[PDB]
Structures are given as C-alpha cells and as structure tokens.
Amino acid sequence: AAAAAALAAALAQAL
Image 1 (spheres, rainbow, N blue to C red):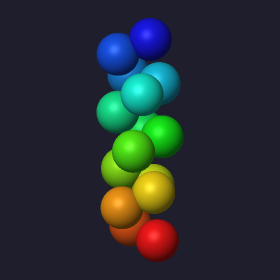
Image 2: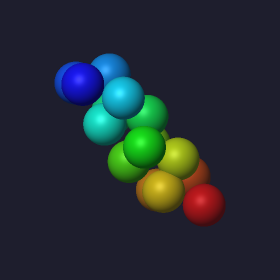
Image 3: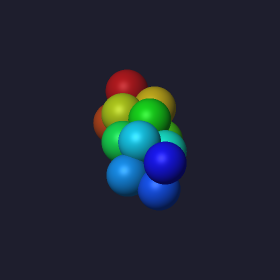
C-alpha cells in the first residue's frame, strides 16, 4: 500500500 500510494502521487505531481 505505502509504495502504491507513493507512486500514484509522484505521477500526479509529475504531470
């Protein structure tokens, strides 16, 4: 879960 969420947000920001 922790990692999944980290990535979800990382990508949202990167956009």
